[PDB]
Amino acid sequence: KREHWATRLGLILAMAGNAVGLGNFLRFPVQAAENGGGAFMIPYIIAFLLVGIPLMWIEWAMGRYGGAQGHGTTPAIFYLLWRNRFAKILGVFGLWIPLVVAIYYVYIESWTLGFAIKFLVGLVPEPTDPDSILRPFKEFLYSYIGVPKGDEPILKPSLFAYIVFLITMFINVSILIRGISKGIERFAKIAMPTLFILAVFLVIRVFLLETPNGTAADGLNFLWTFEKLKDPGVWIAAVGQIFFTLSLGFGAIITYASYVRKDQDIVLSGLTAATLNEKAEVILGGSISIPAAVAFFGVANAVAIAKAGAFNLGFITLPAIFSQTAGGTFLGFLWFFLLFFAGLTSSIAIMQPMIAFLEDELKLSRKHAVLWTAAIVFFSAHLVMFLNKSLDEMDFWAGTIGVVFFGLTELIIFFWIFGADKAWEEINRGGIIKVPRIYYYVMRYITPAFLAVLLVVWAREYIPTHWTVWITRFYIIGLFLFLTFLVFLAERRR
Ligand SMILES: CCCCCCCCO[C@@H]1O[C@H](CO)[C@@H](O)[C@H](O)[C@H]1O
Ligand SMILES: CCCCCCCCO[C@@H]1O[C@H](CO)[C@@H](O)[C@H](O)[C@H]1O
Ligand SMILES: CCCCCCCCO[C@@H]1O[C@H](CO)[C@@H](O)[C@H](O)[C@H]1O
Ligand SMILES: CCCCCCCCO[C@@H]1O[C@H](CO)[C@@H](O)[C@H](O)[C@H]1O
């Protein structure tokens, strides 16, 4: 009937693996560094317990419920929880958001593969002061991406970058066309321990760094210790970070859970996978980028450096640091290959909702479903590769506002429209362990308030222009119109 996860471990590794690629290998330190160290940890762990842990369980319960019904996509599951025609249109978001993200994320996943190859081969620029070293790497990334000089709205991507984009798309297709058990699960069971050893090695190797300008021990000292706690800005930063910590709102959790059998546990399994992301992110992610950045530029600059961006830190600053340390070019290969494997576990997960839609609703073969999903993602990506602000616009609508708005939609449908006490049964059913019943009050009231707070602060910021962003808006609007036509074509089949 429906493909199911062969192993309980592989299910956890695959579920843990999708949030691994969502930046947090380098993303947590930047968001920390902006908020400082032990400042960030208190709202962030609190947000992890208050928002991520409940909302994750909400996503698991919705997906498995749909799997028994035979649907792993949001438009159908929303209709099962809420028998209303507006629910299917809202469901298109949970199909729209991962698709738009996939369009721009797989291309970023190519950059790690292309760099790793160039670092492996040694085709890397090699040069006291920060500006002397960072410029040859800024140009190296910019030549690769094809970023134009200054303002110009057209990118000239490298042929090498384009050839790698074909290879990158192909590798996903290879993993996806095999299915859940022989594709994602086999790869997750391979990729996740590969990431552990790579991170642990890098963490140990980063730990030994020391320069006349600073010491990597001070970078760790930075990460662990008001009045930032009193400043409302930090609570905003941590909650949005939890979404990427656990891949909430992207709809990836809902789809993977649909392949869980009707009576298998989600409580212990989801908590475990949620814990794996935390340990990887707090320990392995925190002890690489910032401690290395602090060791070379001093404690003060890395904070200012991290404010510039994660790409500057991840794709320019960190590779420049490795070039100066002893061996050296090899570390750059590891760091980017580490990012590439993490991207694979996520890119295969972020394209799964679209694939499951074609199989479940349009009754396409998985071979056809994967290839038509790959074609949509590959074709649309040309918009991201050649338009200057296109990547940023999609990431703002799908990756930022959308994931928060969609998570808030999940709670209201599953815990309010569906019936909270009805839903509490679905979370804990077949659970090896079962949720503490304090969360019933948190899932019902405390968690939705926080998601509501997050949306209004951004609306306060963004309720009040380059032309190229309108093309990107116009395009993703059509995608939503297109996916609505597919929900319409599928609802008229029966
Ligand atoms: C393989 C992919 C590498 C992971 C890099 C993604 C880390 C995300 O990076 C962050 O994305 C935010 C957008 O919401 C930006 O506002 C931030 O400047 C940036 O730090
Ligand atoms: C097989 C997928 C469609 C192929 C047609 C895409 C045409 C764009 O391919 C272009 O080739 C140029 C060669 O120098 C590169 O400079 C460009 O960056 C690249 O986008
Ligand atoms: C990169 C940070 C995430 C690392 C995920 C590593 C997942 C651990 O890996 C798993 O651990 C189990 C024991 O706990 C073993 O039984 C499994 O063989 C192994 O796959
Ligand atoms: C642009 C994406 C289109 C997908 C490529 C489909 C190629 C033709 O698909 C065909 O469908 C048949 C029915 O299962 C199979 O028996 C054939 O092996 C296959 O070649």
Image (cartoon, grey):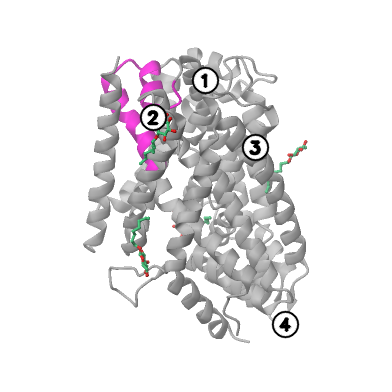
Of the pair 71 and 265, the residue shown nearer to us: 71
Mark 2 to mark 4: distance in Å? 58 Å
Disc 2 residue: CB within 8 Å of ligand 4: no
1 or 2: tag closer to the N-terminus: 1
* In this view, the mark in front (2 or 4): 2
Q: Indicate the secondary structure of the residue bearing disc 4.
A: loop
Q: Which residue is mark 4?
A: 212
The magenta segment: 71-99
Marks 2 and 4 in Cβ contact (< 8 Å)? no
- Residue at image location 26% in from the left, 58% down from the top: 469
Residue 43 can be seen, yes or no = no
What type is the residue that disc 4 sits on?
Pro
In the rendered image, which residue does mark 2 sit on? 358
Alpha-carbon span between mark 1 and mark 2? 14 Å
- Judged from the image, the secondary structure of the residue bearing numbered disc 2 is helix
- Looking at the rendered structure, the kind of residue marked 3 is Arg
415 in relation to 374, above or below: above
Return the x and y of residue 268 as percentages of the image width and height: 67, 26
The residue that mark 1 highlights is 2
Between residues 186 and 105, which one lies in front from this camera angle? 186
Kindly report which numbered mark, 4 or 3, lies closer to the viewer in this rendering.
3
CA separation in Å, label 2 and label 3: 23 Å
Asked whether the residues under the numbered discs 1 and 2 touch, taking CB atoms below 8 Å apart as contact, a structural biologist would say: no
Q: Name the residue tied to disc 3.
A: 186
Marks 1 and 3, how far apart in space? 18 Å
What's under tag 1, amino acid-wise? Arg
Nearer to us of marks 4 and 1 is: 1
